[PDB]
Length: 587
Ligand SMILES: *[C@@H]1O[C@H](CO[C@@H]2O[C@@H](C)[C@@H](O)[C@@H](O)[C@@H]2O)[C@@H](O[C@@H]2O[C@H](CO)[C@@H](O[C@@H]3O[C@H](CO[C@H]4O[C@H](CO)[C@@H](O)[C@H](O)[C@@H]4O[C@@H]4O[C@H](CO)[C@@H](O)[C@H](O)[C@H]4NC(C)=O)[C@@H](O)[C@H](O[C@H]4O[C@H](CO)[C@@H](O)[C@H](O)[C@@H]4O[C@@H]4O[C@H](CO)[C@@H](O)[C@H](O)[C@H]4NC(C)=O)[C@@H]3O)[C@H](O)[C@H]2NC(C)=O)[C@H](O)[C@H]1NC(C)=O
Ligand SMILES: *[C@@H]1O[C@H](CO)[C@@H](O[C@@H]2O[C@H](CO)[C@@H](O[C@@H]3O[C@H](CO)[C@@H](O)[C@H](O)[C@@H]3O)[C@H](O)[C@H]2NC(C)=O)[C@H](O)[C@H]1NC(C)=O
Ligand SMILES: [Cl-]
Ligand SMILES: [Cl-]
Ligand SMILES: [Zn+2]
Image (cartoon, rainbow, N blue to C red; front, side, top):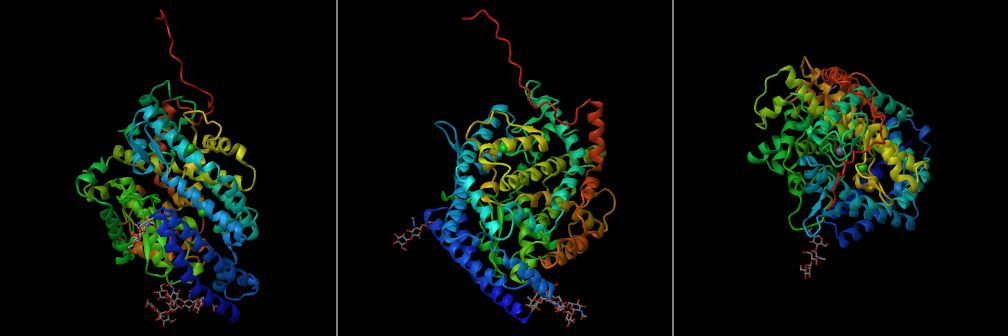
């Protein structure tokens, strides 16, 4: 037992130096994609693997079930997982090269107008999807992004799957999805997620039908079938994963302009997020954060990984965000999400290295989103002068719940299906011959969406979603959206807020800060249900908090759709627009 403690000390001390090295290399590539920065990162990938290999093989000489201290037990179980360092060196080199090629391909992909400008995903294509109301322009960006990014990833993915599965098996799992699912250490995970998804089906179906009706009156009866799926390019988002950018088309009864005109900048957006955390009594970000973060897209023509991300450099002092920030409300919410990762990093920085993780990955994703729920309320937005004051009517409540639902509820089936697809790719039930076909089968089944153009040989639409080529698990985001409302509910009840949950603003609540702090400080030292119960008072994942938040909207949608005679669901997937009659005479 004294030997295991000696091992843990050596692991924590030595791991910090090598992980900090790798983080630095990984950052230098992410903020400057070049052949030199790529070469260095692959180099350091070898170095970190030799460390993982050294201490992982030692960790596997202990019998953890014979250890008394439960904290030391959890640590050694973690270190026994070699992850990709389990692969032989030649295969590891190939695997690391593949991950980098896929990540680079995605990040430098562009969609060009013939003899015109070339658009990048951020901000150009993102802005088209969010603001264009013309069927053909939206289709140009939607299909263009999948031709350039999606198709370009297909040649890598079969070998990526082969190798990530091999690493998992060498670490004792059945496949890579088994390894990923183990992050929640819950035997019943798949059933729990299925039941959570089913609890939210009534709400999503009613939202789907109402939004389908709104699109029907804007884009025309010839392009929207009221008993079928929605074309995937009309929801305001490249992946139809959140719908709030079409609030204008669906509101039942402009913040970007306000942020720009009033002088908001990327650094002021992250500062406002920082001020919100400190209003709760949580930690401010160090001066080194403002010094080293990349909070704007470079202007020197540098190629970078623009997708927002938060970084821990494993020295208790250096935490950074890398985001190509745009001055709008959407990205203000992203900034809060990213600042929640940083808060977590700082909260558990003094824990042993292997326990410096979220209670589960969903917890890490939820912290920032919890605060953003309060920032997004009309009261708080007005306090930020981004909205003129509103009266708290019934019609303004439904409008606000609708806005929130277009993001939170619409995201539920998308976040669910991403890893349903990957899990089945990893376990072998989906192969390269039907990657795209099963992707759209799930897009239909769970989201009720259809592709606006036929998918041809060589399409790989999963590859056009950042997390697929980047190999970042996605179920964490499904979990996050459920539990962030459980957290919101608990923090609001703690702060004394009474009444409708959607009117709660935990701004300045030191009680809410203390509750989040003690949970984040646990890191990964206790199974996540204990952290769940500390915050909420119960140990389970439950959709009830989310459903309580949206109860007024669910009631309103059910009535509205019933009186309009809507068919909930989409039984008619095989429909087309009518072909207008071509009458003569013919020149
Ligand atoms: C199994 O092993 C684990 C692990 O051991 C640890 O990890 C391994 C890998 C090795 O490295 C070990 O050497 C190492 O010790 C054992 O778990 C440990 O158990 C001890 C004993 O209970 C704990 O000590 C207590 O910690 C609490 C909490 O303090 C931490 O957290 C605070 C925030 O939550 C933070 O502010 C603190 O600075 C401190 O932070 C920790 O610091 C250590 C040292 O660097 C670090 O290793 C941890 O990672 C780090 N954790 C975090 C989250 O940052 C503390 O409250 C206790 O002191 C109180 O009580 C004393 C009397 O009992 C009293 O003298 C103190 O002044 C203090 O008193 C309280 O003070 C507050 C505020 O000042 C006041 O409001 C209260 O009124 C007052 N109360 C009283 C009564 O006066 C004490 O220090 C370890 O934290 C814990 N470590 C871990 C990682 O969990 C476990 O015991 C083993 N099990 C068995 C069966 O043997
Ligand atoms: C992004 O990465 C590229 C490539 O890694 C960086 O370009 C490199 O920048 C250094 C420093 O400017 C160049 O170093 C050399 O400086 C000496 C004098 O000090 C001079 O004699 C050399 O001829 C050269 O200028 C290096 O050559 C250069 N490499 C290339 C291929 O251009 C770049 O700095 C990075 N951008 C960042 C971090 O913003
Ligand atoms: Cl798609
Ligand atoms: Cl995950
Ligand atoms: Zn995140």
